Image (spheres, grey):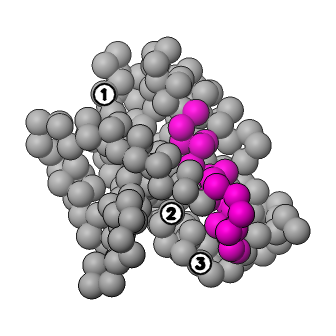
Amino acid sequence: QLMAFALGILSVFSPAVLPVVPLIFAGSRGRALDAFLIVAGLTISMLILGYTASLFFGFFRVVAMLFLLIFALILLSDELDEKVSIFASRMTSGLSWKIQTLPSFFFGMLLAFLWLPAILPFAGIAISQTLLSENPLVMLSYGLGMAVTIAAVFKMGEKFVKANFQLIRKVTGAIVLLYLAYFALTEVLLLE
């Protein structure tokens, strides 16, 4: 949304684990603020795709995601763990082009990169949905992933949690859902 980016900054407030190690998908530093801008960034380029650009910045979408992969590499670096291993699994579900790819910037590789920036912005579109047209399909698909994640993060407003091991699990569901919603060959237009 035109304020979802702002929503993340509030999240940054909530300190939490001093190391704030990628756990609450939050943050607690100056450099982190710069990273927050990136999550917001993914939605604007993509919106043009909604129908069929062919005269905007279609190329920008692939390169933009490439820079993001660098941030993703740190997650894999982790000293092995659960969700991290499963997180890689999203790549198998997410990728598609294989026995029929279009020689370019490895479109499919780029897509895997794309999921990590979102989430709170993904949360931002949903707020828009309640006060905008109708489409329970996204909500129903989104709802199971959304309810667990939204409740845990809300706690941050007052103060995050020690480092609830359960909380990390919520992050994966939101990420899996976003790719499917974008695929929806409908909506995402609205603006004439």
Most extreme residue toward the right, as rendered? 192
Mark positioned earlier in the residue sequence (1 or 2):
1
Q: Which residue is mark 2?
A: 178
Whether residue 151 is visible, yes or no, is no
**With 3 as the anchor, is 95 left or right in this view?**
left
**Of 45 and 82, the residue lying toward us:** 45
Residue 30 drawn at (x, y percent):
49, 14
Do labels 1 and 2 touch, CB within 8 Å?
A: no
> Which residue type does callout 3 highlight?
Ala
Q: Residue at x 11, y 43 (%)?
A: 80
- According to the picture, the residue beneath numbered tag 3 turns out to be 184
Q: Is residue 113 left or right of residue 130?
A: left
Q: Label 3 to label 2, Cα distance in Å?
A: 10 Å
Q: Which residue is mark 1?
A: 21
Q: Which residues are magenta?
A: 37-57
Q: Please name the residue shown 36% across and 71% down the image.
A: 103
Q: Position of residue 65 (x, y in %)?
A: 45, 49
